[PDB]
Length: 270
Length: 270
Ligand SMILES: OC[C@H]1O[C@@](CO)(O[C@H]2O[C@H](CO)[C@@H](O)[C@H](O)[C@H]2O)[C@@H](O)[C@@H]1O
Ligand SMILES: OC[C@H]1O[C@@](CO)(O[C@H]2O[C@H](CO)[C@@H](O)[C@H](O)[C@H]2O)[C@@H](O)[C@@H]1O
Image 1 (tube, each protein chain N blue to C red):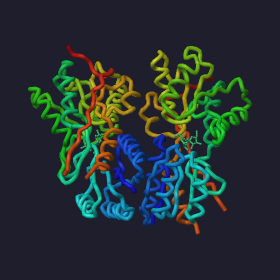
Image 2: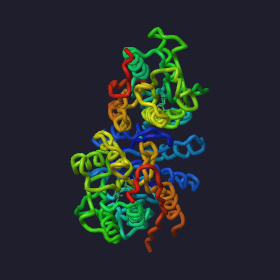
Image 3: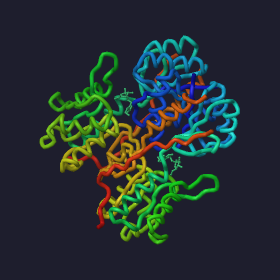
Image 4: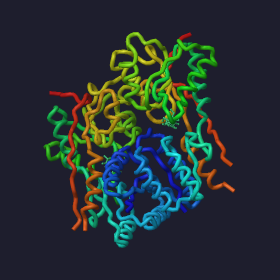
């Protein structure tokens, strides 16, 4: 009675919150939780897999998009359950996640309602060979669904880091003439980067830039101004993923509701 | 070949940094790392221990002071190496750590050089039945070694949380008439709580209160003003500990140096 969790080496604090949920469901069901990290080296990846098989895990919960297909296949082929959390990793397996389009669309809805038209997505916005650019694509769809045009849509960044937020409006764009009035930050720390870059250059959020972040973890509460955020229920995602495994005997996608918490980082332009 | 790491369910971000160092050393030596979390429920602790025994781990690295003695004894009695990190858990086992007294005394030295006499320790300052009040005792020793008196020594708090920092100067002392000019925060988040409580009540750091934190993780760089801090080398603690396990052919304490990084959160009162 052991389940494994594969966590990327480089992660936001979302993982810890998911783990808290997994743990409370595992503990009350008589299972124990084995946590292992996954880097980008295919040979270390295979060792990690030998660790999962050797501890005879019943299930493996995947929190990383960098999981090689062969690991998913090999686990399934050993009759181990594989479930992905916060991401749709393979058509072969079930997933528990917040609904990405609904999250993004709720933010765009709100920003447009507050009078914003020129809006940037800042954070993980890159196109790649093997990973869907989920947030970039949803942002663009939502903006165009709202009858805005390419000229209103701005993008910056390759990851969810503080530094990406900070650099976006200092070296990515001209901080004195930002061409957008609002930024959607793909993670909380990106929002914190944006706040500090503005403050460090004689400007203030939200007067000079409105910000909404995705995740709603503790950084949004300790930021000043406090950050408006889409709060994900990471612990519920963890609980529901474990429950799915426990209740199992067709792959399924379960969407966990989110909510937009309004704090102090958005200005009404109307 | 597998090694375990036992992490408290409630932890600062220091654990991930330790684990980064453990991870790089385990990888290069052909071991795999299993991470497990420990609550304060003794039955759950025991179930976990059976997860360490039955994974036939070669070593267990302990990050938490809440480890029951029976767990350390049972692991040693099964010929498993046990090494504690950042804390001296038991006289029976080796430890790798920053030197606590030197960290504390480095801060007190500096604040006194900067003209401060009335100084608070804010954060984990409580006395208990089973756990040494390490920082409380070191602060008092260092202050008195510098020929300051009990009337110059102020203490607040029971843990390393943001909330403890925030409440210290709102419920703990009168924010308009603080009896100390500087606070030593026992973790970075406690410092951030102090900054926000001051700012939220119309005050300014460092003019109205000087702050120095212990740990020197990312929050100290994100804070405005940037926090003066004693930076611990958490990855190196992890690396050195794993290497101690790999080299073993009697219990020792290995101390890893720290550095006081002077930033923008301390006023020179001279
Ligand atoms: O941009 C979304 C994209 O990034 C990943 C991590 O690579 O998202 C994880 O991290 C985000 C920031 O903390 C979370 O908001 C998200 O829920 C989580 O999955 C990918 O998983 C995702 O496709
Ligand atoms: O106050 C020191 C005391 O607290 C513990 C945690 O209970 O310290 C850990 O967390 C601190 C704050 O992040 C770190 O500065 C410290 O290095 C780490 O050990 C105990 O271990 C320690 O005795």
